[PDB]
Structure formats: C-alpha cells, structure tokens
Amino acid sequence: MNIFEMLRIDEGLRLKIYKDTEGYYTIGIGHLLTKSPSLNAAKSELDKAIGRNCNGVITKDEAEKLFNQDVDAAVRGILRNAKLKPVYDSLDAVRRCALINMVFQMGETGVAGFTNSLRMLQQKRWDEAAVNLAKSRWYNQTPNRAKRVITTFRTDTWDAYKNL
C-alpha cells in the first residue's frame, strides 16, 4: 500500500460537490473547496481550480489531478514546517504516511498543534503517542479514520487498511 491508496480509502471518491463530515464543500478525493456556506462560492472555487466551467461536476481524471496536487502540497508543507520536518525525518516510511494522512485532513497548522504527540512520536514512544493522539477532537469526530491512522503509528504495519 502507499499514501495514495491509503488516502483514497479514508477519503473516498465523489465526482459531485459534496459536504465534509464538517459540513464543508468538497469534491473528488477529499479536496476541500471552501469553508463558506454558499454552494455558489464552492462552484466558483471549483471552476477556478479546474480551469473550466464544471457546474459542480468533475471527471475521474480531474479528481486524480487535484489529488496528486494535494498530496504533493501536504508533503512539501511538512518539509517547510519547523515543527513537522524533524518529526517526519525521524520516522520510517509507513509512519511517514500516517503523518501525511493527518496533514492532508487537518492541515499543517492543525497537526503542528499536536505538540505532545509529536514529541512522543519523535521519541519513538508508539504506545504513549497512540493514547495522546486519541485525546482529541479529531478522534472524537472521525473515530474510525483516527483509529486506522493511530494503528498505523502504533504498529508500523498497514493492517488497519488490510481490513479496508
């Protein structure tokens, strides 16, 4: 399994504008369009993003294009972030995927706020970090996904996605 397969299990694929678990306007593979309540503002962002008049609908192709860009941006942002970089560098491949997954869902900023857990991942205290990560809004709001990610950090294997 790789980062793209992992995220695609967690995010799913929708070719029509839809609402986040959060109520936000999204499309494709977890590509957030706007936090604004107007379907019109979301439509506008979409067309801006794709470079065409979409009318709220995209092709598989366009979805995957946005996905490649979003993954690329997540990694780069990790790399540019003074708090994320050292953690990422300290981790092995599988675990790096788990961090990337968090960044994709919650943004650089969001994850950089998990100070204590980051410290614990850096120290390679897997069990301790899994307990701390669970004490969050994140886990309470999207428990099945948080659990898969947390398992990955804990175990260093892809078994949580084995099932899925």
Image (cartoon, grey):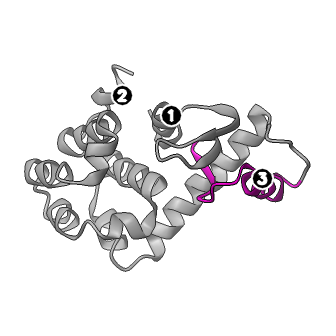
Q: Residues within 10 Å of mark 1 (few under 14, many from 20)?
A: few
The image shows residue 127 at horizontal and vertical percentages of 9, 47
Does residue 32 show up magenta in the picture? yes
Outermost residue toward the right in this view: 53
Q: Which mark is residue 5?
A: 1
Q: Earlier in the sequence, mark 1 or mark 2?
A: 1
> Which residue range is magenta in the image?
30-51
- Contact between marks 2 and 3 (CB within 8 A): the answer is no
- Contact between marks 1 and 2 (CB within 8 A): the answer is yes
Question: Which residue matches tag 2?
Answer: 161
Residue 87, picture quadrant: bottom left
Question: Marks 1 and 2, Cα distance to the nearest angstrom?
Answer: 9 Å
Question: Which residue matches tag 3?
Answer: 40
- Contact between marks 1 and 3 (CB within 8 A): the answer is no
In this rendering, the answer to whether 97 lies above or below 48 is above
Question: Marks 2 and 3, Cα distance to the nearest angstrom?
Answer: 36 Å
* Badge 1 amino acid: Glu
**In what element is the residue under mark 1?**
helix
- Nearer to us in this view, 70 or 55: 55
Residue at point 37%, 80% (across, down): 82
Drawn side of residue 25 relative to residue 112, left or right: right
